Image (cartoon, rainbow over the protein chains, first blue to last red):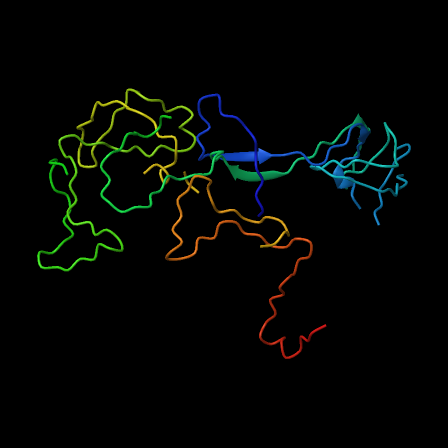
Length: 85
Length: 47
Length: 86
Length: 52
C-alpha cells in the first residue's frame, strides 16, 4: 500500500484513535459532460439506432466511474445506445 | 440491446481504501535510569 | 509491596538471578479482596458503551448466578494499547 | 547525511532513546530523484540474464 493521512478534529467527544474508517475519496471529477452507460463499450466502436437498423458511433473516450463514462465527441443528447447487448 | 438519453451531467468518481484513526501526536513516556518506581500520579483516560 | 494475597512465584530458593540486564520478577503480589473484569467491547459498540451503565454478567462457572454490577469507566485506546478484529 | 527526501521517521519528539546497546535509527533518508528496481530473477534464467 502507501498510506494516506487525514486532518480531522475530535471535539465531538470520541473518535478513539483505534477505529477504522471506510474511506471514499474523490478523483477526478468533471462538471457537465456527456453520458452513455459503460456497457456500451466495444478501437473502440459503438452502435446508434435511428429510427427503430442500428448505425454505429466510433468515439473517444473516458473517463469512467463507476459504470458510466464521460463522452467527448460525440454523440449529443436524446440519442440512441446499446448497453448491452 | 437498449437505450438512453445523454446528460448534461457530471461524473464525480470515487476510490475506496480502508484506513485507521490514530492520535495526532506521536509519543511514549520512557525512562532512562534504573531504580524501583514508587510514585504514579495518573490513572488512565484523563488529561 | 501489597497484602492482597500471592498469585505467582516464579523463583526457586537456591537459584542464581541476574538483575543487572533485565529485572527478574520474583514473587507476583496482587489484591484479591476486590477484582475487576475487563469487558472486551468491539469497535462498533463503543460509540454507544458509556461509563456507569447498568451492566450485568455471569461467571463461566455459574448456571445462574447473574452478577448485578455497573460499568465504571472507559479506556481511550484499544485492548492492545491500553495496558484486524479490534 | 543526504537530501533525496524523507521516507520514514520512527521517532517521537519527547521520547527517551538507548543507543549504547543497539543503534536507534531516528530518521530514514534516501534519494528519490532516481530510483532503482530490483528484478527478482530465478535460478534457471540467470545462466542467461546478462548486464546491459
